[PDB]
Amino acid sequence: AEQVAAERAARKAANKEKRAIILERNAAYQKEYETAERNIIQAKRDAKAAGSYYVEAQHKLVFVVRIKGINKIPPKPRKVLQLLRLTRINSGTFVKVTKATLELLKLIEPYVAYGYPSYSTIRQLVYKRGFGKINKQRVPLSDNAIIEANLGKYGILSIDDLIHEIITVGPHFKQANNFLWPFKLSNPSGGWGVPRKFKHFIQGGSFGNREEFINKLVKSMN
Amino acid sequence: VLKKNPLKNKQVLLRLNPYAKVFAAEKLGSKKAEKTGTKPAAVFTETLKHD
Amino acid sequence: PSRFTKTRKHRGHVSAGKGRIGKHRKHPGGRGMAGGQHHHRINMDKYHPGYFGKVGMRYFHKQQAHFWKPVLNLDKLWTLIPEDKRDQYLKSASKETAPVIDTLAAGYGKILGKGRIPNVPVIVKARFVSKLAEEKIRAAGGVVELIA
Amino acid sequence: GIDHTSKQHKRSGHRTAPKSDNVYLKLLVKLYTFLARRTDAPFNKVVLKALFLSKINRPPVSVSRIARALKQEGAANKTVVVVGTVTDDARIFEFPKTTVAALRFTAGARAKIVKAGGECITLDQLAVRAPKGQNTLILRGPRNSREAVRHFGMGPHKGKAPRILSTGRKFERARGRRRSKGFKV
Amino acid sequence: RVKANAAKRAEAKAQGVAVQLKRQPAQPRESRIVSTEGNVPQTLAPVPYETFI
Amino acid sequence: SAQKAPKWYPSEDVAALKKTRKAARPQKLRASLVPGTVLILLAGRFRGKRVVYLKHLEDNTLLISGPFKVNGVPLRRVNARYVIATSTKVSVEGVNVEKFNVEYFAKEEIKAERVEDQKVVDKALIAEIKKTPLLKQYLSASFSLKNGDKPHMLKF
RNA sequence: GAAAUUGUUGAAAGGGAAGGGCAUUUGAUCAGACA
RNA sequence: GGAAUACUGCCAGCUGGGACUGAGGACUGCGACGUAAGUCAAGGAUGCUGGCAUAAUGGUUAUAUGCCGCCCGUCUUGAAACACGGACCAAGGAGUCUAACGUCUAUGCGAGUGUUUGGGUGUAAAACCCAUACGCGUAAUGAAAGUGAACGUAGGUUGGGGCCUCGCAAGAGGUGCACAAUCGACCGAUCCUGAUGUCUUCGGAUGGAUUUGAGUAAGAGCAUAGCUGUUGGGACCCGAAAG
RNA sequence: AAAUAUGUAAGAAGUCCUUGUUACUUAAUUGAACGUGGACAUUUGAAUGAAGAGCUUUUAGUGGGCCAUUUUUGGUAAGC
RNA sequence: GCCCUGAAAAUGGAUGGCGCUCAAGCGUGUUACCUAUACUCUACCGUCAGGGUUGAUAUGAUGCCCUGACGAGUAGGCAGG
Ligand SMILES: [Mg+2]
Ligand SMILES: [Mg+2]
Ligand SMILES: [Mg+2]
Ligand SMILES: [Mg+2]
Ligand SMILES: [Mg+2]
Ligand SMILES: [Mg+2]
Ligand SMILES: [Mg+2]
Ligand SMILES: [Mg+2]
Ligand SMILES: [Mg+2]
Ligand SMILES: [Mg+2]
Ligand SMILES: [Mg+2]
Ligand SMILES: [Mg+2]
Ligand SMILES: [Mg+2]
Ligand SMILES: [Mg+2]
Ligand SMILES: [Mg+2]
Ligand SMILES: [Mg+2]
Ligand SMILES: [Mg+2]
Ligand SMILES: [Mg+2]
Ligand SMILES: [Mg+2]
Ligand SMILES: [Mg+2]
Ligand SMILES: [Mg+2]
Ligand SMILES: [Mg+2]
Ligand SMILES: [Mg+2]
Ligand SMILES: [Mg+2]
Ligand SMILES: [Mg+2]
Ligand SMILES: [Mg+2]
Ligand SMILES: [Mg+2]
Ligand SMILES: [Mg+2]
Ligand SMILES: [Mg+2]
Ligand SMILES: [Mg+2]
Ligand SMILES: [Mg+2]
Ligand SMILES: [Mg+2]
Ligand SMILES: [Mg+2]
Ligand SMILES: [Mg+2]
Ligand SMILES: [Mg+2]
Ligand SMILES: [Mg+2]
Ligand SMILES: [Mg+2]
Ligand SMILES: [Mg+2]
Ligand SMILES: [Mg+2]
Ligand SMILES: [Mg+2]
Ligand SMILES: [Mg+2]
Ligand SMILES: [Mg+2]
Ligand SMILES: [Mg+2]
Ligand SMILES: [Mg+2]
Ligand SMILES: [Mg+2]
Ligand SMILES: [Mg+2]
Ligand SMILES: [Mg+2]
Ligand SMILES: [Mg+2]
Ligand SMILES: [Mg+2]
Ligand SMILES: [Mg+2]
Ligand SMILES: [Mg+2]
Ligand SMILES: [Mg+2]
Ligand SMILES: [Mg+2]
Ligand SMILES: [Mg+2]
Ligand SMILES: [Mg+2]
Ligand SMILES: [Mg+2]
Ligand SMILES: [Mg+2]
Ligand SMILES: [Mg+2]
Ligand SMILES: [Mg+2]
Ligand SMILES: [Mg+2]
Ligand SMILES: [Mg+2]
Ligand SMILES: [Mg+2]
Ligand SMILES: [Mg+2]
Ligand SMILES: [Mg+2]
Ligand SMILES: [Mg+2]
Ligand SMILES: [Mg+2]
Ligand SMILES: [Mg+2]
Ligand SMILES: [Mg+2]
Ligand SMILES: [Mg+2]
Ligand SMILES: [Mg+2]
Ligand SMILES: [Mg+2]
């Protein structure tokens, strides 16, 4: 009975192959990411050049935070807060945007904060507070093997492979996203920057869509 | 038994994401963007400074 | 036993699992089947339709046993023959020497026919038979011999 | 706090042991807990639960209900498993051969079975003769032939047999049972 | 929708696979460029209070 | 029996530890701590003594001396965290000090070896100290906070 | 020979009730463990 | 014209001070650094040094201090209540037993089951044994006179665990108990139909019908026990004015 | 003639093809219903969620309610 | 707009009290800072749940081990003691 280092090699040697793949993968997302970022920047200028205005596509992904406690909530929002897995305060989940989710958000605005997340904040959410739902349980990620285990079914075999699937709202975004246990943030470290939380953002409160300004918050709460 | 952050703890940083070496190696996080000098049409400015 | 009993559990709880509002008093519905037609009628129709009133003829001094007449179905029939004795007759199934069965002597009154007896001929003695009980017997070449 | 979507600390509500206290049962169960953990065969998982089953859920399988299930097309050599007791049925004359594997065989049952050159088998014997339950036929007793269910479901227009002692006419057969006494059910 | 489906289902099977025939909710719209040619932005401002009665 | 004894006992077979991963790595000193520097002893026996820094010992302690003859403090060990590093600095390039190790202070009146050692180092130091005027007197004086001092403001 | 309740002796506290919770000063008192 | 800066954002840039925690207990995993042997901050604290070895640390207790703290029981929408009981302490002090029962469960035997009215017997109210009967079940349905459960593999259809065959696997087929849905068949009641026949008014074959039954369609019951529940009893305990 | 509220549908119990059964039905092998044989798998026919779904039996307490924003009746009003 | 008049009740008395006047008042803006049985991370208890493990030749198989979530409570149910 060999295996001593025998099959021990026939793994590690093949453990290397799989990092390699990941390395070539991650390296390439970068090219993608920046040279799309870059692409808009010069779009915006190129239209300014022409006198024309360049309107970038509506955001496709949002990140939501239950900003309100548990009690004295009316039934229909109460459900939607469930269906969106925000069943306790300061917990957050990703939402793919279409009308048929938009209307959901609509309905729960005075109970949540939400907006558009950078790669930076998606990257840091997943790294530090990312957990998988595996037979319920809620497993911390912390080794890419865990992801391949469950999400490999759809491509996706690295924590960054996860992230790429989120941020780009992939074809497998349902499975990808749901795979992540609703994040559990602490309270913001500065504070809310408002004297009173439960007004709209636009009115100097915290709830509703605050667009790119969601990154400043989530980061304070991460 | 004890979750370790990546983001700090370079060890597990590299355990996920083998790219973090080369990223860091090639100061990727500070890419000096290539310089173009396109100038905006006078429509754009006139109307920016309109009333 | 007293010790597995829930009143032991209730010790230390004021109300004995009887509630503080509505207590445990003497007889609130009334005693017994009171208010059958009145405040417990809902219960009596459903759970007990048919309860009130009257149907059918009165029979003064009915003596049961007048009407004694236990039924044995063909269903069994062969049961009445002891199992050792039994197989001997099933195989070797003919007239000339076919088993007699005094079903009165079993303790039955009528032979009904719940169906399927092997083609063995049998001489069946009873007080009473179903029209089919007989046919079935006769199709095996048995007969029914009426006794009392 | 958490908007609970579901009741907290619910028990699965499925049995886990027999509520029995008989060693021998306890042992058989030892066998099949082992056998069902380590053998990826469905039959063992099924059998294990059936041992936890209580008397009601173990209605008797009869030897005549057995003979029928062998009359099953292509099923004449499989071995009937019964996680309960087997009873005799005088109503069938030409019971077949085979192999019955049960918890208990009534005297008449086991008699009839062997009288035609069959074999009666404790389940642990069944275990060793066929770990993965290969070539088994599990039969089940008629659960709903209990007298008690006659009375389940009672109410108007339900056709369901009163909970009633002494019966005959004069026993709930008037008002509410016939169009000429108030009404009908 | 079914007989609609069953057609492009075959029509694209007999072609070269590649179907996609679940309905999808309204997607947020794409980027686009708006020209100024013939269309300079007309600046507006709030009005003062009047009555006319 | 008064009590009915268990049906189980703990094994008294003690486990061995897990193979811990904690390298004792070398302690790099705060920048103000350069040989030749005058320290202020914030505590202990010679609390408030101003005193010259000589060598970093392999048990992280500091090698100081008064010099003895100036202020009475001898060649000694001192923890680097109970000390105020000042800004003033003599030259220790002529003081040997390599002799002095941890074992040199193993507990095991005064061993004349020390009494000799202590004369030799000091004689070198006073040579240097005599260079900058009023230093010797500086060293001889104890440090104390006076009404008004805010260390969180004071430069040393 | 319990309790309520009482005499004595000892200790202690007390600016219009007493008793209680968390916490530590102080006093009194006590375990365990060192080897 | 060419810069700078602010502002917003990014870095898998570097780096300082401080606070809480140190679960785990051989090894095993994922990695990192090394040309290398190795090493490591990579599946949870170790290294070095000192103090007391004691009332030092710690418990308990009394008091002082900061903040906080209304009387319990009860009925009630609502009690600290200007609602009721309660001055104090001991000892008593309230869901029981029984007859008959529903669900559930355990156990014995099983188309049966129940020794204990009784008899036999005894180390004598026990334990041991047992004949005949009886009760409940094994047949239903009509007010009754009465009649009484297979067209068929004890039926067709659909779902169905499990097993069987094919396949490496995915899958496909075969068979399918319990159970559930639906269409039917059989028995009695009701209504219709009324063959062969006859002591000419008896007989009721056969085939039917938006009718109907606590039914049949390869039995599940009987007995002991228990928690909970039901009724009658002084009926959880104490209470009338009366008769 | 709104807003809110509210019925149904979004497939395998689906869509087509061929052509049996009957006492109903048709001028009619016409049709109605129930079938036999065949053709098409999970982008099999929107979203999000699901610590699974379904089902059965038995039994407690309760059957004086009160408050808030909004809708609203009586009343001049009311801590009505 | 703020302020003043309009502006009358019974024990002495209430922006909560002292007191405050370029406020410690009114309207508005910007930061910082204080602290809930809530949130985040960790230990420990218990409840529910999903895994693993009858292999002797030592000690609980209702056991042993890994892991995840959760924890308000009258009347009332059940359970373990
Ligand atoms: Mg979501
Ligand atoms: Mg900060
Ligand atoms: Mg802060
Ligand atoms: Mg700050
Ligand atoms: Mg405020
Ligand atoms: Mg944070
Ligand atoms: Mg007892
Ligand atoms: Mg009792
Ligand atoms: Mg008890
Ligand atoms: Mg209780
Ligand atoms: Mg109690
Ligand atoms: Mg209670
Ligand atoms: Mg009390
Ligand atoms: Mg009760
Ligand atoms: Mg009471
Ligand atoms: Mg009441
Ligand atoms: Mg009556
Ligand atoms: Mg009769
Ligand atoms: Mg029968
Ligand atoms: Mg019956
Ligand atoms: Mg029956
Ligand atoms: Mg090491
Ligand atoms: Mg250092
Ligand atoms: Mg001096
Ligand atoms: Mg005495
Ligand atoms: Mg204390
Ligand atoms: Mg440790
Ligand atoms: Mg430890
Ligand atoms: Mg001591
Ligand atoms: Mg001491
Ligand atoms: Mg005292
Ligand atoms: Mg005290
Ligand atoms: Mg107070
Ligand atoms: Mg009261
Ligand atoms: Mg009142
Ligand atoms: Mg009270
Ligand atoms: Mg009052
Ligand atoms: Mg009263
Ligand atoms: Mg009183
Ligand atoms: Mg007492
Ligand atoms: Mg006697
Ligand atoms: Mg005897
Ligand atoms: Mg006799
Ligand atoms: Mg009977
Ligand atoms: Mg007649
Ligand atoms: Mg059919
Ligand atoms: Mg199949
Ligand atoms: Mg079939
Ligand atoms: Mg009929
Ligand atoms: Mg009728
Ligand atoms: Mg009946
Ligand atoms: Mg009663
Ligand atoms: Mg009285
Ligand atoms: Mg009287
Ligand atoms: Mg009278
Ligand atoms: Mg709707
Ligand atoms: Mg709806
Ligand atoms: Mg859907
Ligand atoms: Mg989902
Ligand atoms: Mg689930
Ligand atoms: Mg109920
Ligand atoms: Mg009720
Ligand atoms: Mg009621
Ligand atoms: Mg409210
Ligand atoms: Mg005022
Ligand atoms: Mg103030
Ligand atoms: Mg102000
Ligand atoms: Mg400030
Ligand atoms: Mg807490
Ligand atoms: Mg609780
Ligand atoms: Mg609860």
Image: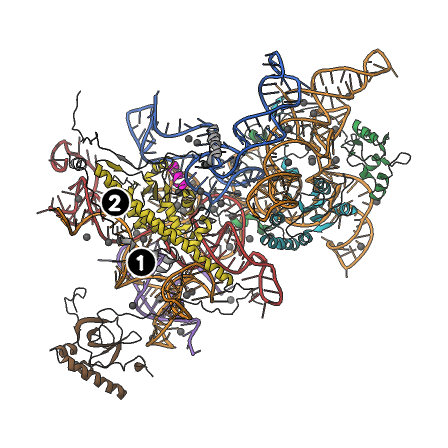
Chain colours: A yellow, C green, D cyan, F brown, G purple, H orange, I blue, J red
The numbered dot on residue A194 is: 2
Position above or below: H236 against H60: above
- At label 2, the amino acid type is Val
Examine the rendering and report whether any part of residue C60 can be seen. yes
Q: Main secondary structure of the magenta part?
A: helix
Q: Quadrant of the C terminus of chain C?
A: top right
Q: Is mark 2 within 8 Å of ligand 5?
A: no
Percent x, y of residue A34: 30, 48
> On the picture, is I54 further left or further right than F103?
right
- Quarter of the rendering containing residue H243: top right
- At label 1, the amino acid type is Ala
> On the picture, is H89 further left or further right than B33?
right
> On the picture, is H211 further left or further right than C70?
left
Percent x, y of residue E49: 16, 27
- Nearer to us of marks 2 and 1 is 1
Percent x, y of residue F119: 21, 85
Query: Quadrant location of ligand 28?
Result: bottom left
At label 1, counting other C-alpha atoms closer than 10 Å, the crowd grade (few under 14, some 14-19, many 20 or more) is few
Percent x, y of residue E24: 41, 34
Observer-nearest of D2 and H165? H165
Position above or below: F9 against F48: above
Observer-nearest of H231 and C75? C75
Asked which secondary structure carries label 1, the reply is helix
- Magenta highlight on residue D110: no
